[PDB]
Length: 76
Image 1 (cartoon, rainbow, N blue to C red):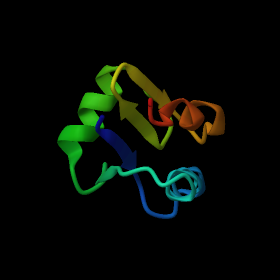
Image 2 (cartoon, helix red, strand yellow):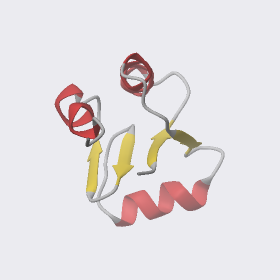
Image 3 (cartoon, rainbow, N blue to C red):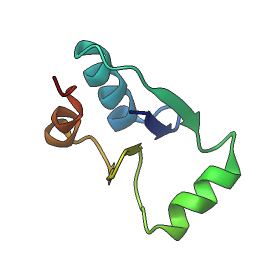
């Protein structure tokens, strides 16, 4: 399952999210929305209003959400 974190530099909630995923041994890709406006536009069209935005399988959320990150633990 691919986990993508849409991020921005100087974004505390983004850093917290990355660190939280690393603390749990998750593999993820990061996409800087300032360097990739196509992604920024796509996220705005889906209604997101804050960063980071995490997309993983059927889940998609914004902001630092430890509770949602915990839903990414691998199945047996």
